[PDB]
Image: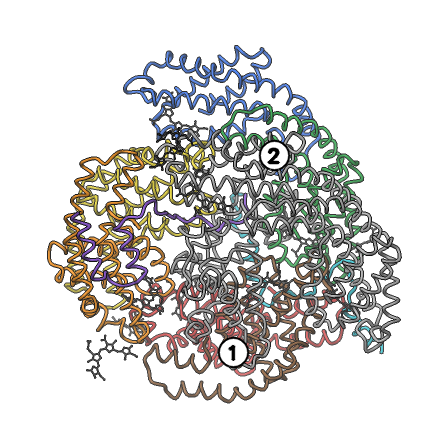
Chain colours: C yellow, D orange, E green, F brown, G red, H blue, J cyan, K purple
Amino acid sequence: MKDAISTVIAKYDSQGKYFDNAAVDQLKAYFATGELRVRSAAAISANAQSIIKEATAKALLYSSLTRTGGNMYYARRFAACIRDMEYFLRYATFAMVAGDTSLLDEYVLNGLKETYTSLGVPIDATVKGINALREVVASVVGPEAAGEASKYFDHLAKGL
Amino acid sequence: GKSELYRREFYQPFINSRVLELAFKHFLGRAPESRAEVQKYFSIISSPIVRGQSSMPSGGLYALIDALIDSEEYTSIFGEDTVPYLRNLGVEAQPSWNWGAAYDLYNYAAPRRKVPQFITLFADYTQPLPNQHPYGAGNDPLEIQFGAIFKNSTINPAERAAPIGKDVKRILIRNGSPTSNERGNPTGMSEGA
Amino acid sequence: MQDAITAVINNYDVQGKYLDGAALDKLKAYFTTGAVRVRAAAVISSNATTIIKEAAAKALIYSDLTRPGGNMYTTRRYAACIRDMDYFLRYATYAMLAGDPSILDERVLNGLKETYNSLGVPIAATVGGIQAMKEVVGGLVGPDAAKEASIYFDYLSSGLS
Amino acid sequence: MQDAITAVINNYDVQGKYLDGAALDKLKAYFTTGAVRVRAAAVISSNATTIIKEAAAKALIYSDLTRPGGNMYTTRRYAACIRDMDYFLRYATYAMLAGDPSILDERVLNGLKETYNSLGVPIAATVGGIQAMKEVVGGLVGPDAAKEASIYFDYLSSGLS
Amino acid sequence: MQDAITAVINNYDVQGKYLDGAALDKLKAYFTTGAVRVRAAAVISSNATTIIKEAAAKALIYSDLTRPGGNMYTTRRYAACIRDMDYFLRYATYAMLAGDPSILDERVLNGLKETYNSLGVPIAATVGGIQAMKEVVGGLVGPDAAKEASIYFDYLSSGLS
Amino acid sequence: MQDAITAVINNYDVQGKYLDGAALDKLKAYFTTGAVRVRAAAVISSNATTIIKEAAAKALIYSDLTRPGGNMYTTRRYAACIRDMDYFLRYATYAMLAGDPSILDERVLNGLKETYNSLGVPIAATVGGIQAMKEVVGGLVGPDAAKEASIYFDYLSSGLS
Amino acid sequence: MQDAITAVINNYDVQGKYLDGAALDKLKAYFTTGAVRVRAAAVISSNATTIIKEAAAKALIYSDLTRPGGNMYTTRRYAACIRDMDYFLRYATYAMLAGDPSILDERVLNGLKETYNSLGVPIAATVGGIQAMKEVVGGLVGPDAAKEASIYFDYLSSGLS
Amino acid sequence: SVLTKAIVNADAEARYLSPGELDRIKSFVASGERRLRIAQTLTEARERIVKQAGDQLFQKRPDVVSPGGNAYGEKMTALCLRDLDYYLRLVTYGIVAGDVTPIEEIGIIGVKEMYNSLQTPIPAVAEGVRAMKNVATSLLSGDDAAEAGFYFDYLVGAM
Amino acid sequence: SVLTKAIVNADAEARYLSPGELDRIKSFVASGERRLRIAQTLTEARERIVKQAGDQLFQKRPDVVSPGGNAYGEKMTALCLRDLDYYLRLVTYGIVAGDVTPIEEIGIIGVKEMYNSLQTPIPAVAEGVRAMKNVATSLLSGDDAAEAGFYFDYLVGAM
Amino acid sequence: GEDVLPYERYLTPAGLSLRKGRFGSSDVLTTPGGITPRGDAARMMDKI
Amino acid sequence: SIRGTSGSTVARPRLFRTVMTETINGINAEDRYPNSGEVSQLDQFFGD
Ligand SMILES: *[C@H](C)[C@H]1/C(=C/c2[nH]c(/C=C3N=C(/C=C4\NC(=O)C(CC)=C4C)C(C)=C\3CCC(=O)O)c(CCC(=O)O)c2C)NC(=O)[C@@H]1C
Ligand SMILES: *[C@H](C)[C@H]1/C(=C/c2[nH]c(/C=C3N=C(/C=C4\NC(=O)C(CC)=C4C)C(C)=C\3CCC(=O)O)c(CCC(=O)O)c2C)NC(=O)[C@@H]1C
Ligand SMILES: *[C@H](C)[C@H]1/C(=C/c2[nH]c(/C=C3N=C(/C=C4\NC(=O)C(CC)=C4C)C(C)=C\3CCC(=O)O)c(CCC(=O)O)c2C)NC(=O)[C@@H]1C
Ligand SMILES: *[C@H](C)[C@H]1/C(=C/c2[nH]c(/C=C3N=C(/C=C4\NC(=O)C(CC)=C4C)C(C)=C\3CCC(=O)O)c(CCC(=O)O)c2C)NC(=O)[C@@H]1C
Ligand SMILES: *[C@H](C)[C@H]1/C(=C/c2[nH]c(/C=C3N=C(/C=C4\NC(=O)C(CC)=C4C)C(C)=C\3CCC(=O)O)c(CCC(=O)O)c2C)NC(=O)[C@@H]1C
Ligand SMILES: *[C@H](C)[C@H]1/C(=C/c2[nH]c(/C=C3N=C(/C=C4\NC(=O)C(CC)=C4C)C(C)=C\3CCC(=O)O)c(CCC(=O)O)c2C)NC(=O)[C@@H]1C
Ligand SMILES: *[C@H](C)[C@H]1/C(=C/c2[nH]c(/C=C3N=C(/C=C4\NC(=O)C(CC)=C4C)C(C)=C\3CCC(=O)O)c(CCC(=O)O)c2C)NC(=O)[C@@H]1C
Ligand SMILES: *[C@H](C)[C@H]1/C(=C/c2[nH]c(/C=C3N=C(/C=C4\NC(=O)C(CC)=C4C)C(C)=C\3CCC(=O)O)c(CCC(=O)O)c2C)NC(=O)[C@@H]1C
Ligand SMILES: *[C@H](C)[C@H]1/C(=C/c2[nH]c(/C=C3N=C(/C=C4\NC(=O)C(CC)=C4C)C(C)=C\3CCC(=O)O)c(CCC(=O)O)c2C)NC(=O)[C@@H]1C
Ligand SMILES: *[C@H](C)[C@H]1/C(=C/c2[nH]c(/C=C3N=C(/C=C4\NC(=O)C(CC)=C4C)C(C)=C\3CCC(=O)O)c(CCC(=O)O)c2C)NC(=O)[C@@H]1C
Ligand SMILES: CCC1=C(C)/C(=C/C2=NC(=C\c3[nH]c(/C=C4\NC(=O)[C@H](C)[C@H]4CC)c(C)c3CCC(=O)O)/C(CCC(=O)O)=C2C)NC1=O
């Protein structure tokens, strides 16, 4: 895929440029942030299961979907939605490390609206669930790394 | 796969990029899932064989078929006993990034489309959006003196859809002097022929 | 477009054959059905606005689609969807009178899938709406007419899907 | 695919409603017809080869199609056409057991039009063959079974046309 | 096209949420940057002709391109190339004010590769010209503005390549 | 695929006509040309690597394409482009032996334009390369063979463009 | 389009070379041929209706095409086919005056194959008609003119096939 | 937004942004912070504005909430109030944008067609928006109210 | 890069990143600043490295710059030096990435095929890279040189 | 404008390739600042 | 949004197995007309 280091490289090779200070500055920035991004990722992995459950509760649960004639309805349907929420989390974490949005869209965003429209899944709800995951994640993560972590969540939300 | 029947029915009527996509579907039950795999396989079928002592023709398209059966993904999921089955919505999850294409590949009408679908889709995601009618590739008439000739969806499926918002503007080439083009100058039509 | 009568004629013309009794029988069959069809068409035309309203109520509205982030959210999108519904109804009525599905293929069906995919309109929901229209239409037209009406609605649905 | 019983269940499940007696009656109706359907299916399976032969004789053979330059000319094409006929028969039998037209839509009807158009197979002739099979089938199955059998054959014909 | 203010609005509209403080903060952030952007845009507009001149001198002219057999040979082609350069500059300026790269995708970037390939215009040379313009622009706008300006120029370059 | 001999046969088969003297004359014409074609094919196979080298030198290499940001920049892309060139050469040789352009349509030509457009490979440059190969091939094969060789190269070029 | 004189000019312009004796010789060659070409063109224009009639008689008419189920069956199709024949004749005449095949490529040849395939017009029959026209034209124009006329007719034929 | 509108006019003219146009952008960015506050005020008072406006509308038009009328019944009355809420949200978006364009795309294009299918009377909807304006004006300070009024008036004009 | 590789392995396993994998990422980010300096040094000395290496190569292989040889002539000699420059740029990219993958995609895949069409001798190219390594090593400090050497060695191995 | 009858003003890239592309691109697609050996050998023969 | 769309396909999954469907699905996979045994199995299912 593409991550912040390789992104800078890739822009330079197409120009045929050797690495400039401007480029070296962007690269330094990643390395400063990186140490805590590693910390924040570990926090999110440990509490993942909890994070999802809290998020579902805030939006997905106690909605029309849970009521019969909604997508959440049934255990089978309920399970699927949780898997999707777990998907969104792993990627967002993978995106937090690396620091490049693109990992997201190659693996998640490309095609999603087309599957969801085909399955009948409601796009808006998923967007709400993602925003919920964002708030829970931010608390666990802590304030400094929250800004970082929020970016990848927002990308996912606007993609859908 | 190596048999005479398998080519001519498949392979011989398709271009090489389309053959590797059908050969995915029937040998492994999935559609081709990424840009890097359709590239690895395109180099296998493309590659002139290393000369083989086995009279059984060396590599070529046979290489393609080998590479699929010899693949761990193949052997593991199917095993030696099972005949390959089509994995589908019910089984093995099914990924979103190739959804639309894959469901077309699974239908029996699939061998009717001759234009490759997977390579076009992968790498249409990496590219900026194309030069085409907003409502679709089929909506652009062929540009000839007289006659309205469109591509018909049924007579040979070759759809290219692209998401083009209300705001997007087509780039059109001026029939005439380039600087006449009205995007760069509003008065260009009121100029000398 | 083509109709039933012309379809028979065209088949004979390519053969170069003069019209024969077997051909005549097919034409005769159409002629009996014709009177029913005309009555059905008049019913549909008069109730067209309501048919669309009822069908939307059954499937499209009070749904995620109409809610924000849904395809039919915003007035512009809502208006587009009901315009499409009207198209389907008008063409189905034409097809029913004609006794031939060809007009649907020539006008509505050709390029619709591709258009919808570019737009991001959901095909399954559209199909649902068409099926809903069929049900409403079935009631108004009455049973004999309903069978004839249903096939064209189903044809549209199959094409889209 | 879907069957009659499941179709009723699904409609009730979205409503959340326990099955109404009226709904139950429709299910009950299906259950009685099911015995007759099974008998019809066995008849069709045993006489399948003959049914196809008779239908071909009625429409396909002794025709321009079989003559050189016709779609069914050459052994390969002839064999293909009779294979398609068998498919239609088998699926119609499946539909009759199911009591639902959906399987026809899911397997047979979907992608058929496109396949045929690329191949240049004539749809009207195919429809003619399906109608011929229906007539032959009607005789063998007997009257009560025939009505049930006919609807699925007609469904196929309408889809193709 | 989209701008930063509208982007925030659109995100909220799909959620259906009323504007909130967090959203307001993003808007506020843009408003502070805005004053700088407006100053940069005015600089670019005034020096546009010179920017193009300098960039062409750096990359395009005094080269094989301008010599016979080169793409920019003949007056008509020369004029076209400088017109294209102006487009890139104007759109980048628009993007910088907007704070969003979307306009570049919707107007400039869409179908450019295909157009150029049909025309036979060399993409890499064009990219070179864009990069040259960026360097000249960076000087005039000054450092704070330059960072903002550079991203849009780079976006164009990446799209074309 | 099809060859000249089979093409004649197929035309007669659709008519249902037995082979006639006029048909025989066309076959006879092919048989005389055959010996020349075989010699040409052997020449091309032996010199294939050089043909590609020379053609690349004439059109592709020492260009924007090879320069950074060009389509053929990077080893991987360079290798891909020469692989494509080899394909064109091999297929043209096949076509020349066959005496029929059909194989080019069935394997090379079908879907290539669309593939290239998605990839962003420049079609006109590729066509240029094909034309260059033709010129080199013409020399090696000699005049009588060259005319035959040229038509297939031109066929490829026209298809791509 | 382009003509022989302009073609020479354009080749020199890309080189940037002033006109040289070798170039002059090509121009001089054209000038001598010119007078003959003008006479030939006038002959063709006057006899155009007959040329088409004769060519149709030789290939198109009294054939399966004209018989029911043939491409040129029905008045509308017959009229279309003779209109196409006229186009080919007029363009070939234009090309002969010009001394360059380019106009054929720009107007007639571009997209013709694809158009014909969609229409289901038979290419080989069309080619046959073009060849027939050539033979008739050859007679009327006389030998010196015939050689010149033939190349353009052959160019059209090669393009279509 | 203001900026989008300016860019669009420039692109049509195929020119760089005019100095005058640039000046208007500068003024807008200064105004924005004040605009944000105005929007915030309306958001907080949103629930009450809708409620008060609804009551006024129903008093003004007894027919709409009558057995014949579209609004009649709890479900229908809720939907009518939901619509009023939607329009208020759009107005807030407009104030921050400084243009009616955001409002216009979401709410004013195809509105006639949508309501005609629903059979809702358009004039009654307009009255509801007018009612909301009056409530909103009272809570807003005079100069703030004038700004808000423009957006409210546009909506009323559009329907 | 290191990070991409780790993520990719995790995604294949369909699991969150292992502690061990995370630790390797941590080590890499710490190393990065040192790596950046090494890359910067080579970039500044790039012009001289290429020049010195070229001379060494031409001394080692007279033939390449001889009438028979590919490199012979000013145009050709320039191209040979340009190639050396390209490889040096790739090496710098590698050092910052911490992986050969960036190098590998741009330079090592299809290299054989490209050079065979050109008819350039692959061993001579390898010698040039070796020469560049020696020059680069001298400018770099010992530990820095070892890091740089790995990437240089990979290139030599690849060709 | 009431007196001119409509004419074809613009065309799409694919339409343009149809008319001009037969025979493809003539030219080598020269770039600025490229080392190229093109034309050298001819210049030497012209000298000789 | 995404640069490219593969498109949307109307797909329905199966909420619950039924004996009716389960028997049919076996028959289709076999591509055989209803086997002798199942016919008996089906009508008891119809009556019961
Ligand atoms: C608690 C001792 C009693 C009780 C109450 C209860 N239920 C839930 C949550 C759910 N129950 C269901 C229901 C079903 N889905 C199915 O597929 C079936 C089988 C036919 C059933 C019965 C589901 C899916 C949930 C989870 C989400 C939802 O509300 O739909 C809760 C809350 C737990 C939660 O929010 O996850 C409670 C308190 N159920 C009993 O029968 C107990 C006696
Ligand atoms: C209230 C002032 C008047 C009124 C309202 C009314 N509306 C509906 C139903 C709908 N109204 C809308 C409108 C919108 N959807 C949008 O996206 C927007 C812009 C963001 C608007 C304005 C929609 C979509 C519906 C349909 C229901 C749904 O959304 O699911 C009703 C009910 C109609 C019915 O009979 O079903 C009513 C009553 N009615 C009046 O007469 C009042 C003056
Ligand atoms: C004679 C050796 C034996 C024989 C012949 C027989 N044939 C038919 C009917 C048909 N024969 C064909 C065969 C072909 N069609 C093709 O395209 C080809 C390959 C080029 C062949 C060989 C066809 C299609 C028919 C169907 C009728 C039609 O032409 O439309 C019959 C008639 C019997 C029937 O129709 O059932 C007969 C008698 N049968 C014998 O007993 C001889 C030993
Ligand atoms: C016979 C009544 C008519 C006819 C038939 C015909 N069909 C083909 C070829 C194909 N038919 C199909 C169709 C199906 N595949 C399926 O899975 C289903 C649903 C279960 C159907 C109905 C397919 C896919 C093919 C192509 C595969 C193959 O090898 O046959 C032909 C041959 C056409 C050709 O030239 O290849 C023919 C002749 N055509 C007629 O003339 C009859 C009216
Ligand atoms: C001489 C009477 C005047 C003059 C000329 C002048 N020209 C340049 C530079 C260029 N002029 C051209 C012109 C052409 N290129 C074409 O394609 C055509 C048509 C075939 C023409 C006429 C070009 C391309 C250049 C740009 C540089 C280049 O060679 O690539 C200059 C110097 C450049 C500069 O202005 O700095 C000059 C001086 N100058 C006068 O004042 C005379 C009146
Ligand atoms: C300049 C750096 C390079 C160059 C340019 C060049 N361009 C053309 C012709 C066209 N350029 C465009 C491009 C655009 N139109 C748009 O709407 C957009 C997005 C806003 C772009 C970028 C178009 C469409 C044309 C052709 C038709 C027209 O302008 O109406 C030419 C002329 C080619 C010809 O012969 O027509 C040239 C030379 N060429 C170079 O060598 C430079 C590297
Ligand atoms: C060389 C003259 C020009 C050129 C070529 C080029 N092609 C590719 C990539 C691909 N080429 C194909 C095409 C084919 N598929 C087929 O079936 C056939 C006929 C048998 C062909 C010719 C395919 C499928 C690919 C993609 C495979 C892959 O990605 O590895 C490239 C690489 C582009 C990329 O982005 O990878 C290139 C460079 N392009 C030029 O610049 C020359 C003018
Ligand atoms: C008879 C009243 C007059 C007459 C007739 C005549 N016709 C031809 C030749 C042709 N006639 C047709 C006409 C048709 N083809 C169609 O498709 C239709 C509609 C279905 C028509 C009416 C055609 C196609 C031909 C061309 C040859 C062919 O049949 O393939 C001739 C001979 C022409 C010749 O000179 O060769 C004649 C004489 N001529 C009269 O003068 C009568 C008054
Ligand atoms: C005559 C020898 C053959 C023949 C011809 C035929 N053509 C058509 C229909 C069309 N022909 C064209 C062709 C062109 N359009 C162009 O722009 C050009 C270049 C100037 C050509 C040559 C077109 C587009 C049509 C369709 C639209 C129209 O006719 O106006 C037909 C009729 C097909 C139909 O169904 O209409 C025919 C019969 N057919 C033969 O069999 C002869 C061998
Ligand atoms: C120098 C050590 C050796 C040498 C080099 C040499 N190279 C060429 C020509 C080319 N070399 C390249 C190589 C690259 N392009 C890429 O994309 C990459 C990776 C980034 C590389 C390394 C290319 C593309 C060319 C082709 C020409 C062009 O630039 O367009 C030559 C001359 C080619 C010729 O034979 O005429 C030479 C001499 N030759 C030696 O003998 C040295 C040992
Ligand atoms: C890696 C990226 C990726 C995504 C995102 C993805 C989505 C995805 N969601 C699916 C199903 C599903 N997804 C949902 C999800 C939801 N329903 C709701 O109402 C909620 C709002 C929402 C989640 C909270 C449901 C309910 C299904 C089952 C379909 C059904 O029968 O309704 C499926 C079908 C696979 C299967 O169930 O076998 C896919 C492909 N797959 C991927 O590869």
Disc 2 is placed on an element classified as helix
Chain label for disc 2 = A
Q: Residues within 10 Å of mark 2 (few under 14, many from 20)?
A: some
Q: Amino acid type of disc 1?
A: Pro
Q: Residues within 10 Å of mark 1 (few under 14, many from 20)?
A: some
Quick check: marks 1 and 2 in contact, CB under 8 Å?
A: no
Q: Height in image: H135 above or below B168?
A: above
Chain label for disc 1 = B
- The image quarter in which residue H61 lies: top left
Q: What is the x, y in percent for residue E5?
A: 61, 30
Q: Nearer the viewer, residue F18 or K23?
A: K23
Q: Amino acid type of disc 2?
A: Ser
Asked if disc 1 is less than 8 Å from ligand 7, the answer is: no
In the rendered image, which quarter contains the N terminus of chain E?
top right
Q: What is the x, y in percent for residue F33?
A: 52, 87
Q: In the image, is C48 to the left or to the right of G40?
A: left
Observer able to see residue J10: no
Q: Residue at x 16, y 58 (%)?
A: D40
Q: Nearer the viewer, residue A77 or H18?
A: A77
From the image, tell me which residue sits under label 1: B57
Q: Height in image: D41 above or below H112?
A: below
Asked if disc 2 is less than 8 Å from ligand 11, the answer is: no
Disc 1 is placed on an element classified as loop
- The image quarter in which residue D136 lies: bottom left
Q: Residue at x 34, y 40 (%)?
A: C129
Q: In the image, is G50 to the left or to the right of B165?
A: left
Ligand 9: quadrant of the figure? bottom left
From the image, tell me which residue sits under label 2: A150
Observer able to see residue E72: yes
Q: CA distance from mark 1 to mark 2?
A: 57 Å
Q: Nearer the viewer, residue E41 or B1?
A: B1
